[PDB]
Image: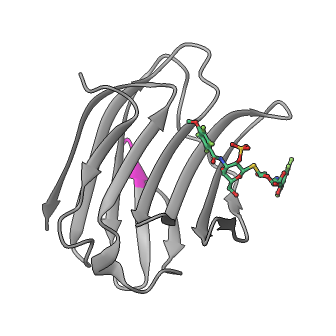
Amino acid sequence: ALIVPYNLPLPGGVVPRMLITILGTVKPNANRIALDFQRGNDVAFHFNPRFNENNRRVIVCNTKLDNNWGREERQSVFPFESGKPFKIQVLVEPDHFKVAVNDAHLLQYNHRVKKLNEISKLGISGDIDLTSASYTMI
Ligand SMILES: COc1c(F)c(F)c(C(=O)N[C@H]2[C@@H](O)[C@@H](CO)O[C@@H](S[C@@H]3O[C@H](CO)[C@H](O)[C@H](NC(=O)c4c(F)c(F)c(OC)c(F)c4F)[C@H]3OS(=O)(=O)O)[C@@H]2O)c(F)c1F
């Protein structure tokens, strides 16, 4: 049981082979969830499940630079369910973040922010009960 929004420091930023694991439960009637991997005020990787965008469920990913959102990356697969426990794993690889939900690969997001070792915070927010947030090197 962690308070949301939660900040997970990433000391010395991220690096390939770093695995971030988030455990929680989606609230009933959730509207959205967000993971924000931040480089100072910039958002290197925003991962944003939306439960009701024009009555569709979609995950939006993007980068924020100098307070400007870039071009969104959207795909169709939506593994979250209101009221249910989830696991998000974010594995940093050399050219992308690799995301799996509930042990199934979901998406990749290519690195736009190049200075990986300055992406030194993960913010976790939105309509979840957050159980734990941690990292390990694999
Ligand atoms: C298929 O359907 C669509 C569509 F319907 C669209 F509208 C778009 C379109 O691009 N929509 C974007 C457009 O309307 C743009 C214009 O400013 O605004 C973004 S919204 C923006 O999108 C960003 C990523 O590009 C962020 O997701 C951003 N959200 C947050 O900052 C945010 C959040 F994600 C949270 F989860 C959150 O609380 C947990 C919160 F407080 C937030 F502020 C969020 O800002 S907020 O909705 O005002 O909060 C739309 O996605 C689209 F591409 C599609 F493909």
Please indicate, yes or no, whether residue 104 appears anywhere in the rendered image: no
In depth, the one of 99 and 135 nearer the eye is 135
In depth, the one of 12 and 32 nearer the eye is 12
Q: Quadrant of the N terminus?
A: top left
The residue at 59%/42% (across/down) is 49
Q: Is residue 32 left or right of residue 22?
A: right
Which quadrant holds residue 118? bottom left
Which quadrant holds residue 87? top left
Q: Where residue 38 sits: x, y (%)?
A: 42, 62
Q: Is residue 58 left or right of residue 88?
A: right
Q: Is residue 6 left or right of residue 44?
A: left
Q: Quadrant of the C terminus?
A: bottom left
> In the current view of this chain or complex, which residue is farthest to the top?
28
The residue at 53%/81% (across/down) is 112
In depth, the one of 72 and 8 nearer the eye is 8
How many dots with numbers?
A: 0
> In the current view of this chain or complex, which residue is farthest to the left?
137
Q: Where residue 31 sits: x, y (%)?
A: 64, 27
Q: Is residue 61 magenta?
A: no
In depth, the one of 129 and 78 nearer the eye is 129
Q: Main secondary structure of the magenta part?
A: strand
